Amino acid sequence: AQDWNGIPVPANPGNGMTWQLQDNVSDSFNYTSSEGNRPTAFTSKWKPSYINGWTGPGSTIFNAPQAWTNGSQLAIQAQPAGNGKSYNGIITSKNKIQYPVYMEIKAKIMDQVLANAFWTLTDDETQEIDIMEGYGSDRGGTWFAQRMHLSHHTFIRNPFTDYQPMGDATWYYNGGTPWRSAYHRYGCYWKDPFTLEYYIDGVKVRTVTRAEIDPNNHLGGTGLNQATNIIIDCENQTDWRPAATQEELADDSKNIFWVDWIRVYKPVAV
Ligand SMILES: [Ca+2]
Ligand code: NA
Image 1 (spheres, protein in one colour):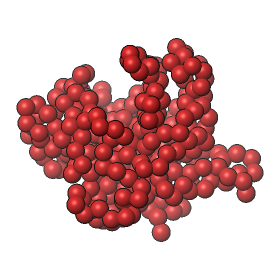
Image 2: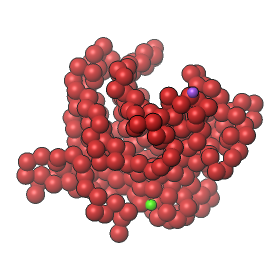
Image 3: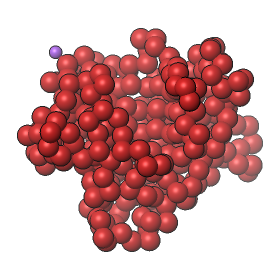
C-alpha cells in the first residue's frame, strides 16, 4: 500500500511506454521519526540538511531537529531562534533524479510569511527547478497568499549571476482561495533539457519551452540536463520579504509545512 495508489499520473509517458515508480525517491512517510530516532525507511532515502554546509538565505538557520514525521506525514517546521531569526526544517534526497521524470508531492503550506518549497538543485548549484514555492500568510500580502510560484533558475557561480523567468504566468492564481487552506498535489514533468510542464491537482497549468529556459546561456547550451538533488524546505527570505515575528515562529498551529507523500515516475517500455 502507498497513499497514492489509484491516482493517475497526468502526463503522457509516450507511445508504447508506461510509468514506473522510482522507489528510492518516493515515500508515503507512514512512520514516526525525529532527531535521535530515525528509522531505515527514512535514512535510506533522505537527510535532514541542505546539499552542503550552507545554513540558508537571509534570516534562515537550517536545523536537523526541525524535520520529523508523525506516523502519516512529514513535518517541515520553523521555530524561534531570537535576534530576528528562525530555525528551519529541510530534507534532501540521498539519490539523484534526471529527465525524463514526473515528480509530485501532496502538501499544505504554512500560515507564515516564510517560503515553503519543493525544488531541485545540482551539486554545482547551476541548475534549479522550482516545482512549487508558496508564501502562506496574509501579513506578507494577500497577493502572495493567493498565488503559487512556478519557476526555475540558471546560475553563473563565482562570480554570481541569477536568471529566472519573470512572466506573469510564473505566479499561479486559484480564484482568490489562499494556498494555506488545503492540501494540493504539486507536480512537474521534466520531459527534456528544454521542456517543463507543471500540474496542480492533476491539471496542467503551465508549460515552459526552449526560449524561456536559458536565454542568456548561463549553462553554455546544455539546458536543464544534469542529474540533480530533490529538496523540500522552508526559508526566512528577508533579503526581500518581511521577517517572521518570533511569536509567529513559536505558534505550533501555524509553523508546519505538512507533506503527506512524494512520488516519482519514469517512462519505460511496455
Ligand atoms: Ca502519508
Ligand atoms: Na494585502
